[PDB]
Amino acid sequence: VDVVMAPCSPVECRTAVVIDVLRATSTIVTALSNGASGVIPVKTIEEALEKKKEGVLICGERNAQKPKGFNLGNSPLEYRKEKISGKTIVLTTTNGTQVIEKIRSEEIIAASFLNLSAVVEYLKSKEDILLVCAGTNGRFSLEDFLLAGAIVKRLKRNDLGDGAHAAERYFESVENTREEIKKHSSHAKRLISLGFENDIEFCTTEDLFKTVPALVNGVFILKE
Amino acid sequence: VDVVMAPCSPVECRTAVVIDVLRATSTIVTALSNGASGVIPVKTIEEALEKKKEGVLICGERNAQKPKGFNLGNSPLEYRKEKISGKTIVLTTTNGTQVIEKIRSEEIIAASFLNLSAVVEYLKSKEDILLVCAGTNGRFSLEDFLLAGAIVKRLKRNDLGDGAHAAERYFESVENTREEIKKHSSHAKRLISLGFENDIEFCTTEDLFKTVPALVNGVFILK
């Protein structure tokens, strides 16, 4: 129904969709689609390190790179079945849990281009929807806004909030998602500079998965 | 160079432009353009009332309506020269000071469609520009975003941040500003329902003024 970019105060809705396309929600979707038991978003590197135990992998990034002592970084390509099947993923990224903590909703799901059609189908029967973009370092995230616009366009609703309308209009101006993000996203440029251009291509590849991660008691999981 | 909508933490930049089109910055521009000595942003109604004294007018809104005890509301049409010329305007709006507090910049100006061209001309020689949209009650503000996009398109810089690129593309999709806002801005629709339709038309009128309000040590003035 509406889109918010990096909210500052608690946002209320019935159905919330978390978007951190350049990797975070793409990592969440990829990990769960490849067998991970669950993905637990955590705020700091320190607390992430305190959660080490058998069957658990400490993952994430800061400055887009894997922190010292961690198992995996925040590149979705690292989350292969042979590496994370049956494991619980403790994930801490730059946006920590900033977005999640401000969401006051009955349901919270994770979206990326990777599972876009599944997300759209799930949302068609939902009311009071808020697409919550995490943003980049508290700034506007082009890739998050683009995914939000793609979703809005396909929900075909008529009660669009300012954010949803702006996102849809922006989406309509895009000729090619991949090219658009590589050329105009600041975070995408940072990722490319660090050798992660492959991540941008993977993260913008639509529908490689048909899953819809749900946040249940602080853990993103797959459920019926 | 970039656009931010209702920032949460302090944003640092060399040059900042505050945007609260539906009234706040339109009121600030209108007031100074009509003779006001300055416009002082104030946080609470309690504080605004205390500053009452000869030569000062207490103005602002809460729920878009003029608070009890106040001289003027937040309708730019109220700031006529015959009423405010030479007086200091104490202005408190819903989240006015909260937004200004997030701007870590030595150079802060206010913009509206009312002084669009003057603002663009002012920014021509400016580097590291951040257009700060106030937003409405924590939500995205279409009218602020549209003005930001209009400014970005006029500057034609070779370095746009994510927000500026999105705002520019959005601006390019709009054929008519007044109709776009009346049809798609939740806040504009609320204002219309409260009887402020004239404000929507006035605030989206381009270049009625050629002034550029500057926040100088807590007070918006015309250098």
Image (cartoon, coloured by chain):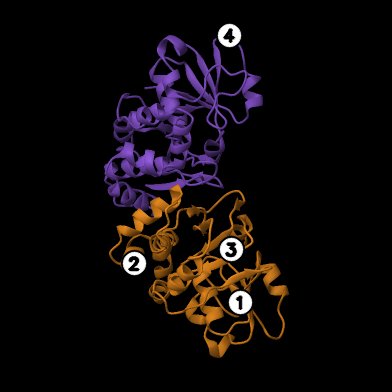
Chain colours: A purple, B orange
Q: How far across and how far down the image is residue B185, in percent?
A: 39, 60
The disc label shown at residue B96, or none: 3
Mark 3 touching mark 1, by CB under 8 A? no
- Chain that bears disc 2: B
A197 and A171: which one is in front?
A: A197
The disc label shown at residue B223, or none: 1
Q: How far across and how far down the image is residue A148, in percent?
A: 37, 42
Q: How far, Cα to Cα, is label 3 from label 2?
A: 24 Å
Q: Is residue A130 visible?
A: no
Residues tagged by mark 3 and mark 1 found on one chain of the structure: yes
**Residue type beneath disc 4:** Glu
- Residue drawn at (56%, 69%), measured in percent from left and top? B61
The mark nearer the N terminus, 3 or 2, is 3
The quadrant in which residue B140 appears is bottom left
The local crowd at label 4, few if under 14, some if 14 to 19, many if 20 or more residues have their Cα within 10 Å, is: few
- Chain that bears disc 1: B
Mark 1 touching mark 4, by CB under 8 A? no
Element at badge 3?
helix
**Residue type beneath disc 1:** Lys
Q: How far, Cα to Cα, is label 3 from label 4?
A: 51 Å
Q: Which residue is mark 4?
A: A54
Q: How far across and how far down the image is residue B100, in percent?
A: 60, 60
Residues tagged by mark 2 and mark 1 found on one chain of the structure: yes
The disc label shown at residue B177, or none: 2
Element at badge 4?
loop
The local crowd at label 2, few if under 14, some if 14 to 19, many if 20 or more residues have their Cα within 10 Å, is: some
Q: Is residue B87 visible?
A: yes
- Chain that bears disc 3: B
Residues tagged by mark 1 and mark 4 found on one chain of the structure: no
Residues tagged by mark 2 and mark 4 found on one chain of the structure: no
Q: How far across and how far down the image is residue B202, in percent?
A: 41, 76
